[PDB]
Image 1: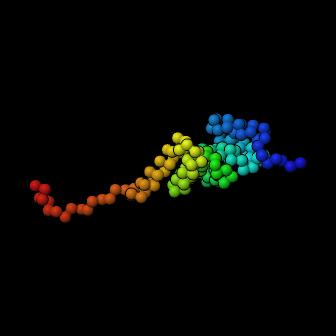
Image 2: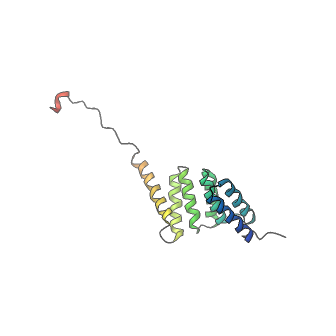
Image 3: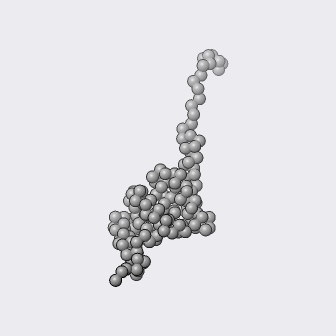
Length: 151
């Protein structure tokens, strides 16, 4: 018969084994274990957001972003997915997109945001303001005054 396409004790075991792999910093294994969980329950936002964390830890920001995005599409009310998406976009230097993700995460979280979301949004805004105001100070003009004018 057909699978239920929803989480099972088996998929959750795989998720837990994935979580343990993360703890050991075995990111490639975590990615594989979360993927196995997702083969049982496709597009599960918890499993997706966990695999996103593993991608991010291993420096694979585009893959992290795709997992996190899909999670936010499936469950836009799941604040953790937005936090994952924010970090992934931040790490891709997509600061506008990171700002948007953190803002939506903060709304979904329903309590002003997790510490990570609040700091994430603050840091992203500061980066955007740095760019807007100029990342480099202006230089003052060279002096055309006479050398003895300071005397």
